[PDB]
Length: 351
Length: 14
Ligand SMILES: COc1ccc(C[NH3+])cc1O
Image (cartoon, rainbow over all chains, first blue to last red; front, side, top):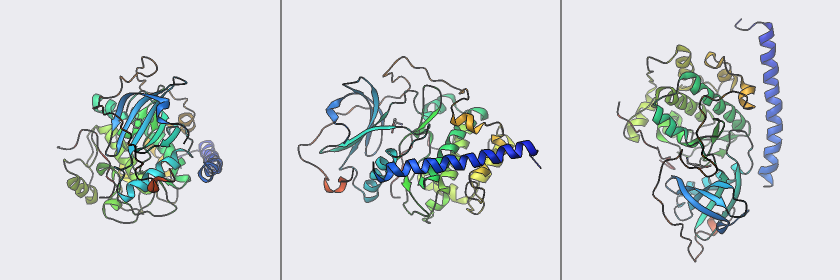
């Protein structure tokens, strides 16, 4: 076979240890999920906007009492107007307050006022993978593989808890002071036992079954991993067009072309992740995540060493001190106005 | 190969 006796026994034992880990992780998650206003706005100085979206922004803030820096996501309650926008915001807070994994951002506080919802997370100063990737062009395969391995382990963890992530992309992956990944933005994450039906995500990263309005499962995350690995290694994603409608047509076609510099091992992995037929997509078969972890492209990956953060990272972001924002792009700054009248109080009672 | 090079916004219901 491909493995000798010693290698096969080591791999098997490793897989049983994964099961043991995930069983304990589920017990810990459920405790926080079943039995979870830990601060207020004037406890922080607002420093700089780190990113912006349709419903709000993320700001670097400094806790007045302790001097610790944090990333504060601010959502305008009125802007959270559409039905699925509201439910998704409750998903995000509840999931972040219950998960625990080395590559998932840690939530520290959450609260709300008359106008906004707030989630205060650890500040990850190394910037988004997105801007490093756009600046360098593309990552070499070993560099892309180091990041991909962290996503594989993170999705193995999330999916074991029946959590789908649903917004993988370089914009949502921050690089920490040791060069490892922190997944942020859980706005589209959801606990799903089987199928779900919401049309959501980012166009370039949508699996065909989402676009086709089919009920779908956690395999959409494995498709998105294929898109991410391709984009990291090529510098652009596999389904690339100026308008969403054209992107969708490419995704559903079932056709992918690869740069001539992609290794054959990489192309094989990507053909099995970017698989329109769900009965054939890696991550969705009887062997689950192990079809990915045991693929030849990952043969050099020490999964436990990655989890334990023992592997030397390919890139360490420069940091000039606490509160440094040099690894983030600049954004238009807008005052945080809080109305004297409570908005949407009933819609956000649970937050 | 024309496509979107800037930050990409997620879509909520379409
Ligand atoms: C720690 O959380 C965040 C930090 C930075 C961004 C911008 N990419 C979004 C976040 O949700």
